[PDB]
Length: 266
DNA sequence: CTCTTTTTTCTCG
DNA sequence: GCGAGAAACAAAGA
Ligand SMILES: *Sc1nc2[nH]cnc2c(=O)[nH]1
Ligand SMILES: O=c1[nH]c(S)nc2[nH]cnc12
Ligand SMILES: O=c1[nH]c(S)nc2[nH]cnc12
Image (cartoon, chains in turn orange, cyan, brown):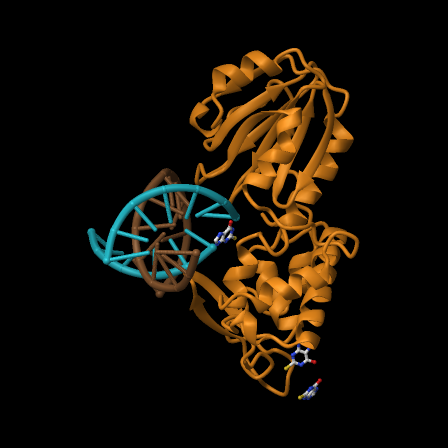
């Protein structure tokens, strides 16, 4: 999932599990709890969920006043709310049991992570990872964005994927964003002119906010509609609606990359 | 059978 | 510092 998918999950969880006391926590794959499963079980059992927040692609469970559970779904992580007698499925790894249901985390590839962080260490946690601003008009300052692009010789797609210029883009939405902003994914950022950076900035915000509104692209959050609106991602050889031009797929910095050459020249 | 394909961090030169 | 490639892992497809 990327930011819109994580936000969709956040919103559904917020509706269902806020106010709920954690009765027990169980793991079949404790190794995904990077801060230590025993510690997390001991600290969180019997606590009440106060809220669910998000920073970039990270889910943040607010559990009691003094702890947060930071969850990353990485490539394939999925949450679901199930009855207490629900059978185990093959790639289920963790469950948070309540009095009247349970929250189960599953992840085929086992990439997703849980970290128990004290409340006053949440802002330092994200500072240490150098996560950039949220993709909103209020938080995403174009002026700083422009200065960082000017000072780098990185290619724009991998630099956007680093999460440092702005938080939340992954492979799908960065491809969508660059098509919308008419920018080549291998464009060196210090070659971008001011008007292109402005369109890029606005496009990042517009695409991600649209995806959030449509419930992401497609367990919780599996009812998304953004997939119907994708212009280039996963559409190799299909039309760009531009006079017969077709989407090409190339590899950029190790990632599958979908773009429309005629639209996205350097 | 092999090889490639699908977020973040780590290693190497 | 940089980029390239690979690591963590599972499953599906060519
Ligand atoms: S360049 C181009 N050609 C078209 N032919 C039908 N519609 C077109 C369009 O929107 N753009
Ligand atoms: O944190 C990252 N997330 C993604 S999607 N791509 C990257 N390339 C380098 N870092 C990152
Ligand atoms: O009208 C457009 N034409 C092309 S070629 N690319 C685009 N990206 C966003 N709009 C367009």
